[PDB]
Image (cartoon, rainbow, N blue to C red; front, side, top):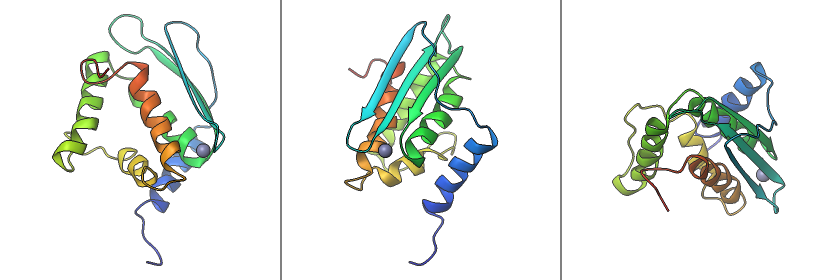
Length: 147
Ligand SMILES: [Zn+2]
């Protein structure tokens, strides 16, 4: 293949959207503080959220590293910042469920999901993919517990 918008144009939009809103790397000490490093690649994402009730009030992502990691976290935490715990647990319940079923999203909203899965498989990109993946699922947990 010469040109394919499979991942290139996808993360292109992911980082460009992140540039239209130039905010990244922050720390909110309140309720949940979960950071995830990739000491091989240099990525470091400190996910500091504030869930004040049964929702998500805010989230600060101190994400450093490469193009995908700091961007994906910012994108998924933006959706989380505007969600609840039920909706977050559901999003991750289906997020993991996709891997058992085949390929499907209840909302069809696979913008980051298809980007994160793209790098998920390359030996060098898998640890940056699992980085954002495991860090987000670890923040508020997933499904109804995960464990
Ligand atoms: Zn990295």
